[PDB]
Image 1 (cartoon, helix red, strand yellow):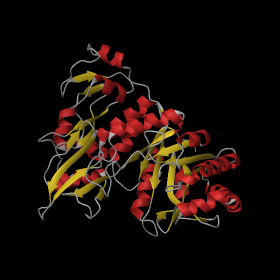
Image 2 (tube, one colour):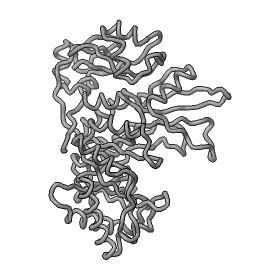
Image 3 (tube, rainbow, N blue to C red):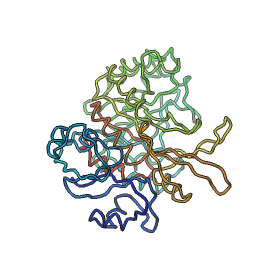
Image 4 (tube, rainbow, N blue to C red):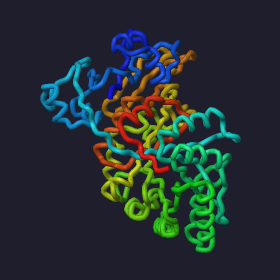
Length: 429
């Protein structure tokens, strides 16, 4: 009960921060996945041991936020510090924080390799993250028009990693043909009973072969005319799954019930059938658009609220990006796509180009701008400990089931440590 988030200020080093808070440099380096030889960046968010039941106020904090973060009732936190519920805080102010009570969470992470065989670095990242997971989602098995599946490479290896860590490997099935989501493919599978029957049979045999106890459909770009056929397919699978198996689906983010591309993702119908959904609450800012926060918290909250109106909250898994993007400016159609960056890589750009990391308190996201060696301006939006803590607190407020991360292979050590600090991670293995 000792870790907190600290934002780096001018002049700070791992040595000075350890001295200030009575920690060790080695601990700060390890917890934050730092290269011990590198400088800290002003505005970088670190996790630091500031002693048990002890907290130093950060920029933008409120007693409400701190109580949400540490799972302590707000009245208790206020009382034990002789403060009012809306009391004005200042940075550096010391608070006593009682031991809170952690709620359970289910966590998912997706793995999507780009090579055959899978890169060693990616297999190592999967092993590192697996202990923090309820589910591991190897993306993907591609559905075929004859009702068979294209298996991704080294499936047995990846499933075994999951199983040995009491993580459930998901059987992730997509309607991808030649690298793109295909409405024509789902029209065949959702409309022909003979093929669909063979398909479901093959899915069950594949799941049983690899110990994949959750069957997950990521069907996208489904024709609107197939909305109810997709619902019927999901009912058909659900009815035939044996005891101990579950069913899940991917949903595009929505904030209302009529808001043609969208229609086939029927929130109400799927919510009645499946065990859980993964809602893709990310890519407001995206690779092909102008620079902005990838998953701004206001719109994400709107999507979660809409989802709760359509289905039970426990069934909802909030999608969360681990990536940010580096955009070259000015944004123009025909520009190259933005470059995806890990949290660690984003900080490394700010370090290299000597700029501080800023924080947007409305979006709840870190960002910065820099000039490269050719004089081209870049803008970066990414994820760090501050914004992930805001997202965890949103999950608590909304009472939803869990969080689903896209994707393994994007270093961000603070995310995984904060996940276990905030929640009890459910293991079903």
